[PDB]
Each structure stands twice: as C-alpha cells, then as structure tokens.
Image (spheres, coloured by chain):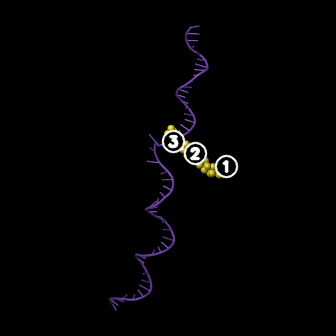
Chain colours: A yellow, B purple
Amino acid sequence: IETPEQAKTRERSEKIKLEFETYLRRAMKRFNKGVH
DNA sequence: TGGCATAGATATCGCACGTCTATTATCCTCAGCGCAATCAGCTGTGACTACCT
C-alpha cells in the first residue's frame, strides 16, 4: 500500500536469496552424504 | 465333539509430498556502411597584352 515497487524488489531479493541458500543447502547435503 | 464366522493384529500398495540437473536455438560490442552545411578546386568569364595586316 506504500511504494509497491519497493515491496516487489524486496520480494525478488528474498526469492533470489532463498534460491541461492536452498541450492547451497542441497550442495552441502550432497557433500556430507558423499563424505559419509 | 467340530464347521467357521468375526474381529485382533500387520503389514502393503497406492496417492500424495520434498528435491535436481538438464532429448535441446540469448544479450551487449565494435567494425562496416549510410546522411547534411563548409570549403576548396575545376571550369567559365572578363581584364590586360601579343601578333598579322
């Protein structure tokens, strides 16, 4: 209801950070499972 | 005594809920072309002077 473009940019930043951190999480799980 | 229903006990297969890397045609950059007011040189014209009569 206030500066919708700022809210959309925040949502995009959250989305890209979430994708980055989730793929990092998957890579870390692959790494430790391979170590085991 | 004996035939077998009726539910206790137990997995069992199906429907549904998480990730993952690619059964195949993009996004900016520099060199190559183009267009419109000066400016200068080729060519035309007048001023000055040579030669035949």
User: Circle 3 marks a residue in which chain?
Assistant: A
Q: In this view, does B3 lie above or below B32?
A: above
Relative to the observer, which residue lies in front, B42 or A21?
A: A21
Relative to the observer, which residue lies in front, A2 or B53?
A: A2
Q: Distance from label 3 to label 2 (Cα)? A: 20 Å
In the displayed structure, does residue B47 sit left or right of residue A4? left
Instruction: Tally the numbered discs.
Output: 3
For the residues labelled 1 and 3, say whether their Cβ atoms are less than 8 Å apart.
no
Residue drawn at the location 67% of the way across and 49% of the way down: A1
Closer mark to the observer between disc 1 and disc 3: 3
Q: In this view, does B41 lie above or below A16?
A: below
For the residues labelled 2 and 1, say whether their Cβ atoms are less than 8 Å apart.
no
The residue that disc 2 covers is A18
Type of residue at label 2?
A: Leu
* Callout 1 secondary element: loop
Q: Distance from label 2 to label 1 (Cα)? A: 24 Å
* Callout 3 secondary element: helix
The residue that disc 1 covers is A1
Q: Are marks 3 and 2 on the same chain?
A: yes
In the displayed structure, does residue B21 sit left or right of residue B16? left
The residue that disc 3 covers is A31
Mark 2 vs mark 1: which is more N-terminal? Answer: 1
